[PDB]
Image (spheres, rainbow, N blue to C red):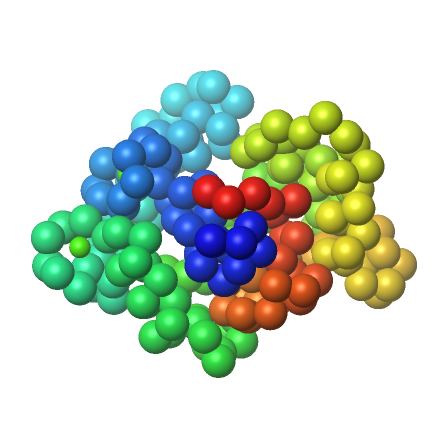
Amino acid sequence: HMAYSWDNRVKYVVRYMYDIDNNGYLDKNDFECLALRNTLIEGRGEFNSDAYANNQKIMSNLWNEIAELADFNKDGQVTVDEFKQAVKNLCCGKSFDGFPPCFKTVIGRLFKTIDINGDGLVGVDEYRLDCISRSAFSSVKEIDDAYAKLCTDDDKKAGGISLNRYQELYAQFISNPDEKCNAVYLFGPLKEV
Ligand SMILES: [Ca+2]
Ligand SMILES: [Ca+2]
Ligand SMILES: [Ca+2]
Ligand SMILES: [Ca+2]
Ligand code: NA
């Protein structure tokens, strides 16, 4: 589908936020791998067995929640189309606070990872590093043009995107069908997945 279509945006979220083993669908192995990845990134490569246990619990609960809401054919996997139906059911027409917990809790964690300097704002430097974590770019101006469209004058006055703003933009990213909405740039310039 068109790069900034709702279909491609939801497919992008499934690919990059959840499908860590890159096999095209979600299952328990993705969440096992996310538990380990989060542990090691939190530890700067150190493995803390208590941090790991905490993360394994968070990710097991997350997977149980997503499968409860999205496993339409009861096969223990959640496809892109199943995830899209859960988004239509539970996100479309709602603001972020009305999303189910399994669609909400993921953002706090991504935001904390992006916010390298811990000042509670994602600024342009942090956004550039986020963008190159998923995709290839030749032009820093392409990334910076996306940040400039994404952010409002109040975001720019603040020096970046706060957590509740990041969540507001995410809610529009995953729910608004308008391909021209500023929030379509949340994860950088897009291509078809
Ligand atoms: Ca997978
Ligand atoms: Ca399924
Ligand atoms: Ca920051
Ligand atoms: Ca920054
Ligand atoms: Na939930």
